[PDB]
Image (tube, rainbow over all chains, first blue to last red; front, top):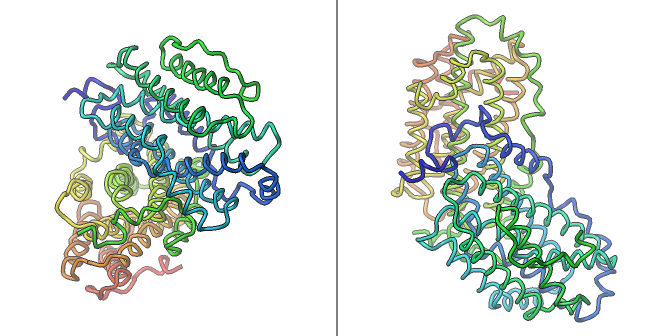
Length: 287
Length: 287
């Protein structure tokens, strides 16, 4: 059928057997993931509580909400996106990569839960926060975007690869940056170190999506790719400049918008297209 | 149906993982994390001289066992990715399955590396990597497993027993045959990797039996027997008729008895009575 045209999707009995290694660049990324293996227990959280206690009320509000939003991502509709890719893609080098991605995303969920438990000890307050957060626009807007660009019956494989790249590389890009801002201020080493590992992992997942894209016979048009990414940028910008403003932790909202656009541009270039925003990176600490 | 089952119920998904609701499932996930290894940790550099001293019959046996294995762990993964990790809703169990997917990919790489090390002729090597089509009894075991993945009809409980049987009856005789080679002091790389892989499969089988305990609605003893007894006959035929263990100097009657011993032990661990009453005939499989 039409998937025989795509080397990535062409059905074979060789999907269960790893050798011979036919895609050395995909394999190298799997080996990179294996080399990055970590577990939640490695992150020392024992020095965070004194730094937590010195944050202002507005800063605690921001951080506790960002953590809750991190936790709620795994719950969303695309709870099985990686598994869906792991099934469609027939190249065993890529299945190995996706297998590790599934494992590490479970480490991320455990890490966020541990963080929330360390900083918000009252289980009544935790329950309040989670129950509120599920009702917020950022959750709903990410789900509708995914319904529209991934779950749609008319979605092509190429479109879904771009969407997956945006999920890994645009969504939460601003939250990772906000936590790097706390690192610049010397606050909360456990939170900031875990953020470094999680951000790195998501960066690797995004790079892998862009590598898959390069192997497509049928790519979506530049116009369509822009629609998908630009829509993601608007959602993320709205969240960190209007709904939960980064001014709450002493950052400038205009520069944050500029950063999210810089991240989108970089994704477009890495997918082989031209920049749309032309935004410079405004953050020296993200250099 | 699945609304009655805590394991399959949408309400069992939780906003965050802690506090742990199923400490015995979580403990097994932590046991799996603690067993992490990679194929590169197994030194294969001393096997080729032993390989070159084996009789023609011994090479035939080992290369065929490897060929079965080469496909097998990949089929187990497809089921987990397609069926189990998706349909189970308890986060402790998803974490376990995520790690099982990773470690099964390590197994496939290990088997590929073994085949690539021992079979230098690329004509013979291509025949072995394509066992799923080029060797009939290997095809039969794979089609048995593949049908339970494609099966829209059978219950989760039935399918968990089936995949417990794949991991605990279908590999059992081959693992034991490789432990026989260890008793004879042959092929340290093959035998050490067998030790790690058999341990992992033992843990996966124990997990299947733990999942089974959490079912409110279990398949009948009759049905469980039918599944396991059928697996036993397939495995017995393979190691006594298609690829006889006499080729590496073992007694076929004792091998049949061992496979039955392993099946009994699975039935007891699932909460049922023994059907074969077979003693373990192999001293080297006690310790």
